[PDB]
């Protein structure tokens, strides 16, 4: 149906906007602390602590499969990256501090992305 095509074109355009949001958020992590999944070989207890691990590579695979239907879903995953790190790691650590900085800087980007998603539809 033509309705299904138009919906898919909207999904595709959301995916475009989310890819750019993702690039801007990742630029706020120059250290690359959040680039890849936590290794269970190197942190064998990780899953006892963290129930839903997340990282920018895993967000990027979901994105390229057009797997985010709305900004809310994308934000949920971004928040997991931050929130997981701030639980596993103590306040005095480079990891925790990096998550705080990513959150604060990411907020700016996400605030305007929400306006763009509403504005364009």
Image (cartoon, helix red, strand yellow):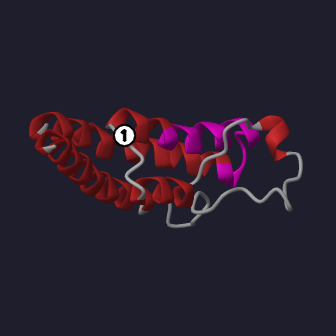
Residue 28 seen anywhere in this rendered image of the structure: no
Residue under the point 32% across and 51% down: 18
Q: Nearer the viewer, residue 33 or 60?
A: 60
Q: In the picture, which quadrant includes the N terminus?
A: top left
Residue under the point 54% across and 43% down: 100
Where is residue 69, by image quadrant?
A: top left
Identify the residue under disc 1: 107
Q: Secondary structure at mark 1?
A: helix
**What's the magenta bit mostly, secondary-structure-wise?**
helix
Q: In the picture, which quadrant includes the C terminus?
A: top left
Residue under the point 58% across and 52% down: 98
- Residue pushed farthest right? 44
**Residue 3, percent across and down?**
14, 39
Report if residue 84 lies within the magenta region: yes
Residue under the point 38% across and 56% down: 22
Q: How many marks?
A: 1
Q: Which region of the structure is painted magenta?
A: 77-95
Is 49 positioned to the left or the right of 28 in the image? right
């Amino acid at each position: 149906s033509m309705e299904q095509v138009a919906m898919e074109l909207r999904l595709t355009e959301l995916t475009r906007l989310l890819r750019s949001v993702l690039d801007q958020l990742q630029d706020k992590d120059p250290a690359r602390i959040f680039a890849q999944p936590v290794s269970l070989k190197e942190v064998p207890d990780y899953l006892d602590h963290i129930k839903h691990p997340m990282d920018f590579a895993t967000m990027r695979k979901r994105l390229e499969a057009q797997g985010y239907k709305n900004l809310h879903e994308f934000e949920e995953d971004f928040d997991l990256i931050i929130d997981n790190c701030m639980k596993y790691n103590a306040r005095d650590t480079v990891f925790y501090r990096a998550a705080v900085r990513l959150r604060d800087q990411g907020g700016v980007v996400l605030r305007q992305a929400r306006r763009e998603v509403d504005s364009i539809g």
